Image (spheres, rainbow, N blue to C red):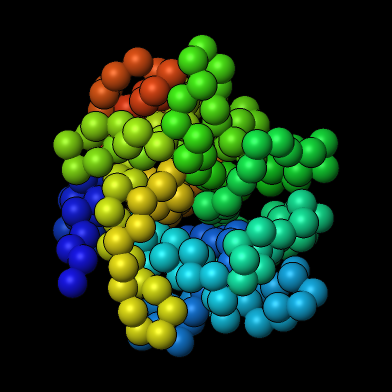
């Protein structure tokens, strides 16, 4: 029975104790959908942009359900939105993802979690995440799982786009997971090793990757906006990046581990 640590590691529970659980914060899980039938997962709304997989509350991959459980473990009162842009196989067209981002914008999502990416992006995709940040949305994305490539950034899109918050993985010891992607694009780190979350069919499992880490930051964003609803995505992002626990060189750790308790008491 996998046991969660990552929530207490970013210091979420300190906010919970003070009554900030992400209430009235719209979090778009732009992923493989969310198994809403999971009794621990409460999904406020959704939309599927996968022509052949038309139910966004049906996660045939399992990845988005894992995302939801972590976002909701960090931010339990957060209105969670199943934006299905990824098929059963966990891949989708950019047009689909863009449609998901477009939707997230259209429906006033406070936070986009895109626990997804790849080696390249597109003008259209950059346009979409930019547009979403211009509209005041906190865009969070996994930095990637490409480890290191010498001096080369291994940070994946859309996380590689300046507008997107790029989230690397540390373990319980704040040690960079060997798989966590690296580059100047790297902003923050968050629990991303053996991360216990919800899986389809009332199941749970540890998963590792910059995706779990991202889900914490998306949750952290939600916690921060539930204390500070009038904070811009800009202020949320600076509060997360500027109060982060310094952990190592920016290329491997960005600013370090997200401390949501510190981020939530930040003075701009
Ligand atoms: Na449910
Ligand atoms: Na970025």
Image spot of residue 150 (x, y percent): 49, 15
Q: Nearer the viewer, residue 153 or 19?
A: 153
Residue drawn at 61 percent across, 71 percent down: 88
Q: At which x and y percent is residue 31?
A: 58, 62
* Rendered view: 31 above or below 203: above
The picture places residue 161, in percent across and down from the top left corner, at 65, 31
Residue 74 picture quarter: bottom left
- On the picture, is 200 further left or further right than 60? left
Residue found at x 73% / y 38%: 121
Q: Nearer the viewer, residue 65 or 130?
A: 65
How far from the left and from the top, in percent, is residue 13? 20, 55
- Looking at the image, residue 64 sits to the left or right of residue 17; the answer is right
Above or below residue 66? Residue 178 is: above
Query: Can the viewer see residue 131?
Result: no
Q: State left or right for residue 237 relative to residue 107.
A: left
Quadrant where the C terminus lies? top left
View extreme (top): residue: 151
Res. 153 in view? yes
């Amino acid at each position: 029975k996998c046991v969660s640590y990552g929530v207490s590691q970013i210091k979420a529970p300190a906010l919970h104790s003070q009554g900030y659980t992400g209430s009235n914060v719209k979090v778009a899980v732009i992923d493989s959908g969310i198994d809403s039938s999971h009794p621990d997962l409460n999904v406020a709304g959704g939309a599927s942009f996968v022509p052949s997989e038309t139910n966004p509350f049906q996660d045939n991959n399992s990845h988005g359900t894992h995302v939801a459980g972590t976002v909701l473990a960090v931010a339990p009162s957060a209105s969670l939105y199943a934006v299905k842009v990824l098929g059963a196989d966990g891949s989708g067209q950019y047009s689909w993802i863009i449609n998901g981002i477009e939707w997230a914008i259209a429906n006033n999502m406070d936070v986009i979690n895109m626990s997804l990416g790849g080696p390249s992006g597109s003008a259209a995709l950059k346009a979409a995440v930019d547009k979403a940040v211009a509209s005041g949305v906190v865009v969070v994305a996994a930095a990637g799982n490409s480890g290191t490539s010498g001096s080369s950034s291994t940070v994946s899109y859309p996380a590689k786009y300046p507008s997107v918050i790029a989230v690397g993985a540390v373990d319980s010891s704040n040690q960079r997971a060997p798989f966590s992607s690296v580059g100047p694009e790297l902003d923050v780190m968050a629990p991303g090793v053996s991360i216990c979350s919800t899986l389809p069919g009332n199941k749970y499992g540890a998963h590792s990757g910059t995706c779990p880490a991202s889900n914490h930051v998306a949750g952290a964003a939600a916690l921060i906006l539930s204390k500070h609803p009038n904070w811009t995505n800009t202020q949320v992002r600076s509060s997360l990046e500027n109060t982060a626990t310094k952990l190592g060189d920016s290329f491997y750790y960005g600013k370090g581990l997200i401390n949501v308790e510190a981020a939530a008491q930040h003075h701009h």
